[PDB]
Length: 259
Ligand SMILES: COc1cc2c(cc1OC)CN(S(N)(=O)=O)CC2
Ligand SMILES: COc1cc2c(cc1OC)CN(S(N)(=O)=O)CC2
Ligand SMILES: [Zn+2]
Image (spheres, protein in one colour):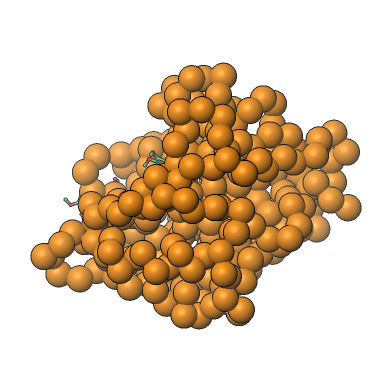
């Protein structure tokens, strides 16, 4: 209900008490064991078509910040790869850490990255996002790791607006943002069936996790860490470590798009 989060007392280890699916058979994130993932020749080429993406607004929802898109038409879509049909971009957000050595949700051979970007798309055959999350193939989330190094120019516009949405419930106009600037060079990926990584933890996501991390600067991620979980006029709780740890793989195979 009201109060799941990422603190010591309402964090991932507590979510199962309100969302029993937390201990389910296809939970996310997972560790990606690179030596055990198998190249899959049946995967079709991945198609990220964001040229007509229409960003609208950026929102601090008390868990992360969301950059929201107009998904009232097929303006920005994800197709191909493991996906059947057309998945429409609705929003992106990140998960990040208090320190550069943690923050990602997925891990790679148990390595944690400083952060992880989630580009969230819903299967248009289900008509709207709320319907799609009730379906095993309702969403496709494109996950991209962030490591700390050189600045990501295409991220800076996001960074510079965070001061205006410091606290929970704050939003700002965020039009004309092009998410293609957040992508790495290669679209090589791993894929597996999983879930939302926050409550309600619905098992409705085809995860597509890019192999190549993007580099962002220390300065850029430091500004992520100045956001607040709390609302305005409440004691400051820095928005850090808003990641769920790796969950049991159970009866799933992670597939690779690349040899
Ligand atoms: C009112 O105090 C609390 C409320 C709740 C939790 C813990 C609390 O004490 C810290 C954890 N749940 S959960 N299972 O993570 O969704 C949500 C509600
Ligand atoms: C708006 O409803 C939600 C949307 C999303 C999430 C949770 C939601 O309800 C809490 C978390 N995921 S994620 N982390 O990529 O698995 C995707 C977007
Ligand atoms: Zn996420």
